[PDB]
Each structure stands twice: as structure tokens, then as C-alpha cells.
Image: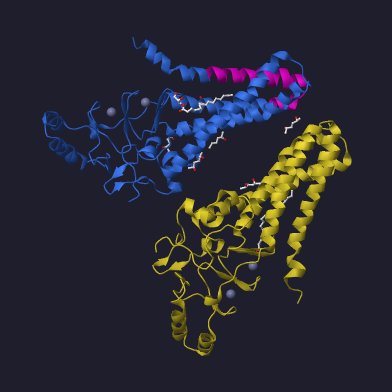
Chain colours: A yellow, B blue
Amino acid sequence: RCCQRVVGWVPVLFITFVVVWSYYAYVVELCVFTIFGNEENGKTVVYLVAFHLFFVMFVWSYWMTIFTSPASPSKEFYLSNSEKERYEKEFSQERQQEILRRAARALPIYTTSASKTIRYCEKCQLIKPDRAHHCSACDSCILKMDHHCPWVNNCVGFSNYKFFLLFLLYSLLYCLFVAATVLEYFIKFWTNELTDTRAKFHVLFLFFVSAMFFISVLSLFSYHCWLVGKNRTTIESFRAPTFSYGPDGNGFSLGCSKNWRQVFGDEKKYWLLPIFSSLGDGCSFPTRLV
Amino acid sequence: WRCCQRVVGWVPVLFITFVVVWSYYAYVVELCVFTIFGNEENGKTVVYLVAFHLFFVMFVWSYWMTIFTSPASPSKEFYLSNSEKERYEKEFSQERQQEILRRAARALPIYTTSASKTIRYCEKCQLIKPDRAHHCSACDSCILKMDHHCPWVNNCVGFSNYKFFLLFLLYSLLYCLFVAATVLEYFIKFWTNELTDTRAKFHVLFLFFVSAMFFISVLSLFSYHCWLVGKNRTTIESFRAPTFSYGPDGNGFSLGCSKNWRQVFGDEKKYWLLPIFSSLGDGCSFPTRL
Ligand SMILES: CCCCCCCC/C=C\CCCCCCCC(=O)OC[C@@H](O)CO
Ligand SMILES: CCCCCCCC/C=C\CCCCCCCC(=O)OC[C@@H](O)CO
Ligand SMILES: C[C@H](O)CC[C@H](C)O
Ligand SMILES: C[C@H](O)CC[C@H](C)O
Ligand SMILES: C[C@H](O)CC[C@H](C)O
Ligand SMILES: C[C@H](O)CC[C@H](C)O
Ligand SMILES: C[C@H](O)CC[C@H](C)O
Ligand SMILES: C[C@H](O)CC[C@H](C)O
Ligand SMILES: [Zn+2]
Ligand SMILES: [Zn+2]
Ligand SMILES: [Zn+2]
Ligand SMILES: [Zn+2]
């Protein structure tokens, strides 16, 4: 059929066109026509330079989140044809899990289903690694899957999670920078200290749209800051993973300081850059116990 | 006699007071009244004056509480009984002296010893030192959860005032930042000769630099203490780690980042930013990691 591309790219292009408009409105309508027209050219240069630094970090982080392909399980997590033949032909439910145990003994998996059964994906025909889940939209198993984000038309998992968090952060700073600088000129237009009708429209919407996204993404950003501190994905935050000693909402937690390092790494120079720096490989994760 | 030494302790406090009193006069009168309101910007004058007083009050309120909150001392239970105190003074063997202390310490909730595995005892105060408590030569007393003695507040920073001390810093950052950000545009205008008043030119110049100097100074102090609170270590413990029954532990009193902050700030969110006492416990016993 039309597949995701026909409609899945719609939220991306909507955000893209809003961001493109915000560039034209802030740079041309505001900085060139409004601020530079008011004979305060010093503020124009500072605003234009500062705006482009936030604009670049946002678009860079947004690009990385969209086009970073989600990681999938390695070869060891696919059932062998010998094991697949017996698994597909087996009728007894108890017998099926016994085949998995022989293959699972080689790989480092510390979690099971809510029924204490080895996590297995029927459509993908493989044994789900720890924290990995199958996405119907992505049609694949995603390592450390968080959720499918329509806004980036991609899965948010082990590969792009830090890019996703930076995409949020730089959206917060971008919207905040716009609202803070536009406010004084938004007020002047409607107290009739400034008159230009073409810029009046863009300056009003620059303030309202940036304030609408700031409030929207701030709660989302604060929520994920809590998730990273607890080392829980969005899926795990609802249905806690079941370990050998039972379900644990803190099974993958290593302490607040260590949990952030798992996502952002140990080198400070990569923390704020949308460059891959997460620890591990996405198939095995350190555990709270052993 | 001591009238020269006691008065000298108030010197750093009075210096801060005169800078703060001047900064009020400079910002409110010289800047808001004479410069901004004189510049026909009557909307900005009211907004700045209202915001300034909110930061000014929170700073002075936190600063007052840190100075005049008397430091807590050990309770009665940590003093040796008259029967035990008499024998302790008469005992000649060093090992025999520890036997009296060890027997009394078994009744008290003590989990730490000195670096020499000796029961912490204060000779001058004649009491058994509670955990994390230390004797201050300036205060001439044992201070519960002592952090350090501060010349800037002429008082010990310990279990009683530590949250007031942290809020005093926090509101110094916000006060200085608010001043520097709002004064900057008028600082620039004076020296591009868009404004002329020589009386206000002087105060606006120092308003920006003094607030920037203190901001840089207290920021490092604030970031350092934010680390201490996250690790549940006092300033003293950050140098000499406390020795527990299982040996010296730099994280002996740590309970995890979230709980360590709660120990200082409490469980009620409505008290976190107010210099009103809300710390957990009593300062004589503390939860342990093990
Ligand atoms: C000045 C303009 C700059 C704006 C750029 C900010 C970009 C923010 C991107 C996204 C914010 C969305 C706020 C979060 C809104 C989440 C609601 C949603 O999309 O539902 C999804 C689920 O129903 C799917 O099952
Ligand atoms: C424009 C308003 C001015 C706001 C004033 C903010 C008040 C900040 C209070 C103290 C800042 C000091 C930062 C510097 C702290 C120095 C470190 C110290 O330990 O000092 C003690 C030793 O020198 C022994 O005396
Ligand atoms: C010259 C102008 O007043 C400076 C603008 C700053 C960034 O606020
Ligand atoms: C633009 C951003 O502030 C760069 C930070 C890196 C870590 O240097
Ligand atoms: C500055 C003001 O006085 C603080 C309020 C407390 C309760 O006294
Ligand atoms: C005011 C302070 O930053 C918040 C403390 C809480 C417990 O994290
Ligand atoms: C000044 C500050 O907004 C007060 C917040 C407290 C927690 O109510
Ligand atoms: C949390 C602490 O108990 C608050 C005390 C004041 C009097 O309300
Ligand atoms: Zn799958
Ligand atoms: Zn997906
Ligand atoms: Zn003492
Ligand atoms: Zn002292």
C-alpha cells in the first residue's frame, strides 16, 4: 500500500515548515525589518548570531533523530533454522519454551515475559534481547526501544535516544530564545509603538507558537529526564520487566549518576552534541543485582 | 578584651550588607527611577521594580536565616551519665576509657568512629560526638552535621542552617543574574552616549560588574555544594571520609541522589525554595547506606 512514507512524513514536514517559517519570521521579519529598522543594529547582530547557534543545534539534533536507523538484534538472537523448524512444528506450549532455553543459554538475557517465559517475537521470529521490543510501525525489533515517535517518523531506541533527548533540549532552548527576544517587540506592536502590519503577524505568531511548543515539549523533556535518571524506557515505565527474582522497576538502574552516563557517555564533549556516545551495545545491559 | 575579636566576626557580614544596601539604592533609585523612568519607559520601570523586590526579599530572607539560625548541638542522650563521667575522668588506661564509651555508644545510634576506630568523644564539650558532628573552635561547641564555619555569615553552617545556606547562595545567583541582565542594556547605552547622567553612570557601571563578580564567585560554590548534597557529604566529609564499622566509606551516608537531596530539603515540595526549616531527621542520627 501507500505505507508509512505517504503519511508518516506528514508530521515531519509540518514541523519542518513551521521551523522554516520561524527562520524567515525571526531573521527577516523581526531582526531585519523590525529590530534593524528601529536603529538598534547592535541587538540585530547579537540576536542573529545567537539565533543561528540555537537553530543549528536544533536542526542537527532533529536530523539525527529522524534518520538514525534503529538498532536491531544481532545474529545470535535469531533462532536457527534447526530451532525454527522445531519451534514452528511444536504444538505443546510447554515444549516450545524448552527449545528457547538451549539457545538462550548462550546469550546474556536476564528478563522474561510477564508469564516468566522467554521473550520471543512471532513476526520477527527471534528471541527479544533485554529491553528490546517489536514495533509494528518500524516492522522490526528495536534495541532498548522507548516508543515510536510520529514527530520524527522513526523509532526512538538505543541508536537515537540521546539524539532524541538533545532534539528536545534544543527545541526548549530554541523556543525559549525566540519567546524571550520577541516579547519586547510583541508588546510594542500591540501597544502601537511599532506599526508594520507584515511583521505584526509574524511577531505575534513567533511569540505564541514558540510558547506553545515550549510548554508542550517542557513536560515531555522533564518526563524523560526522570526516565533517564531511573534508567527506564517508556515501555518499562508502564510494564516493568520481569527478572529472575520477579518484576523490578529498577532492574536496570545503576544509580542516578551512572544511569545518565549509560545514555550520554563519559566524555563531556559529546554530552550536548548529537553524536553517538551511548555505552554498551543495546543487546545486554548492566543490572542492579547481578 | 574580646570586644575586638567578636566585633571582627561581623565584618564580612556588614560588608555584604553595605553592598546589598547600595545595590538596592543603585538599582531602584539610580536605575529604575532616574534612568528607566526618566527615559519615558514607564512600563519597564514597574516590571523591573516588582521583580527586583521579589529577588531582593528572598535573598535577604535566606541571608538572615543563615546568619541568625543558632547551630544545633547534641542532645542530652549523648552526654555521659554522672556515674560514667566520674569513672571516665579517673580512668588511667586508655583501653579502659574506651570501654566506658563503647558501652554507652551501644545505647546511642552511632555508626561511625574516628580514623583510629575510637569512639568519637569531645573533651572540651565532655560528650560523645554524634555521627557527622564536629567541634568548632570558633563556635566553641559541637555542631550537628557540621559542614564548615563561615565568615560570610559569621556562623557555623550545619544541620540547622544548611538549607538556608544553600538557598542564600541560590538567591544570590538569581539576584546577581537578574541585576546584570537588566542593567546590561542601560550599561551599554551610557557608554555609547545614548544617556548622559553622570551620577547614574557610575552606579550603573558598578551595578553590572559587582553583580557579575559575585555571580561568578558564588556559582562555583553553588555547583560544589550541589555535588555535596547529591553525594550526601558535608564539606568536612569531602576531605576526611567517615570511618564506619566496615572501614572508611566516602558514601556511608548516601541514600541515592533523590533521597540525599530530600534529606536536606525535605519531602514537601512547597518548602524547597523557602528558608524555613524542612530537613529530615534531628541531626544526631542519619540513615546509612548499609
Ligand atoms: C518556533 C517553532 C519551533 C518548534 C519546534 C519544536 C518541535 C517540537 C516537536 C514535537 C512536540 C510535540 C509535543 C508532544 C505532543 C505529543 C502528542 C502526540 O503527538 O501524540 C502521539 C501519540 O498519539 C502517538 O501514538
Ligand atoms: C550586587 C549584590 C551583591 C550580592 C552579594 C552576594 C553575597 C555572596 C556572599 C559571599 C560571596 C563570597 C564568594 C567567595 C567565597 C570565598 C571562599 C571562602 O571560603 O571565603 C572564606 C575565606 O575567605 C575566609 O574568610
Ligand atoms: C546594544 C544592545 O543594547 C545590546 C543587546 C544585548 C544582547 O542585550
Ligand atoms: C553548542 C553546544 O553548547 C556545544 C557543547 C559541546 C559539548 O561542546
Ligand atoms: C522577609 C520576610 O520577613 C520573611 C518572612 C518570614 C516568615 O519572617
Ligand atoms: C531547591 C532545590 O534545587 C530543590 C531540592 C529538591 C529536593 O531536589
Ligand atoms: C520565590 C519562589 O517562587 C517561591 C517558591 C516557593 C516554593 O513557593
Ligand atoms: C517540614 C517541616 O516540618 C516544616 C515545619 C514548618 C513549621 O512548617
Ligand atoms: Zn519483532
Ligand atoms: Zn516505530
Ligand atoms: Zn565539642
Ligand atoms: Zn563555627
Q: Quadrant of the C terminus of chain A?
A: bottom left
Q: Is A74 left or right of B84, judged from the image as shown?
A: right
Q: Position of residue B138 (x, y in %)?
A: 35, 23
Q: Is A116 left or right of A223, judged from the image as shown?
A: left
Magenta span contains residue A175 = no
Point 57% across, 26% down: residue: B56
Point 56% across, 54% down: residue: A264
Q: Quadrant of the N terminus of chain A?
A: bottom right
Q: Position of residue B90 (x, y in %)?
A: 11, 29
Residue A188, located in which quarter of the rendered image? Answer: top right
Which residues are the magenta region?
A: B17-46
Q: Is residue A211 visible?
A: no
The chief SS type of the magenta part is helix
Q: Nearer the viewer, residue A192 or B261?
A: B261
Tell me: residue B51, above or below residue B117.
Answer: above
Q: Is residue B68 visible?
A: yes
